[PDB]
Image: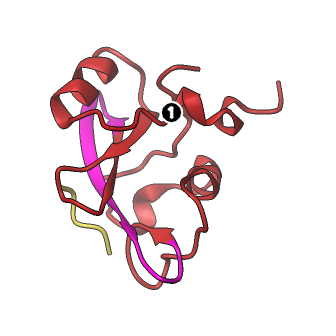
Amino acid sequence: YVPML
Amino acid sequence: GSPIPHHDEKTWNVGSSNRNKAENLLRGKRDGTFLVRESSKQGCYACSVVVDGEVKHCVINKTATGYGFAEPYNLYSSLKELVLHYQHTSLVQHNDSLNVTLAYPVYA
């Protein structure tokens, strides 16, 4: 999954 | 014009749909077309959204303070509230690759 910060 | 289609949760909440089904539904759709589904990561949901012609998948966490993409933004009491927030707010604040909003429910 796309890393979300 | 309004209300926007996002208010009818059926237009974007596809329940227990897996990744491959999500990609099939979003195939060929315009940027910003999205859905919300259960994730293979038990206990979690996922947002699948078309960005630059490609489908991307993001986990939605559920915490004691609400749903969200990441701390300290797990602030929404329902998936609908999350969706409505990110219909006007770009996901780019969480990842520079995601310059899109949740603009178009897959089934609106």
- The residue that appears at 48% across and 83% down in the rendered structure is B64
Quadrant of residue A3 within the rendered picture? bottom left
User: Where does the image place residue B25, in percent across and percent down from the top left?
Assistant: 32, 19
Magenta stretch containing residue B33, yes or no? no
Residue nearest the observer in this picture, B94 or B3: B3
Q: Quadrant of residue B103?
A: top right
> Residue at 25% across / 42% down in the picture?
B56
Q: Which chain letter matches label 1?
A: B
Q: Which chain is yellow?
A: A
Horizontal side of B84 relative to A1 (left or right) equals right
Depth check, front residue: A5 or B47: B47
Please say if B80 is above or below B32: below
Snapshot quadrant of residue B62: bottom left
Residue at 51% over, 20% down? B107
| Above or below, comparing residue B48 to residue B79 in the picture | above
Q: Main secondary structure of the magenta part?
A: strand
Q: Secondary structure at mark 1?
A: loop
What residue does disc 1 label? B12
- Callout 1, which amino acid? Trp
| B42 with respect to B72 (left or right) | left
Please indicate whether residue B59 sits to the left or right of residue B13 in the image. left
Badge 1 crowding class, 10 Å Cα cut-off, few under 14, some 14 to 19, many 20 or more, is: many
Kindly indicate which chain is depicted in red in the rendered structure: B
State yes or no: residue B65 in magenta: yes
* Magenta range: B49-66
The answer to whether B86 appears left or right of B99 in the picture is: right
Residue B82 location (% of width, % of height): 57, 58
For the N terminus of chain B, which image quadrant? top right
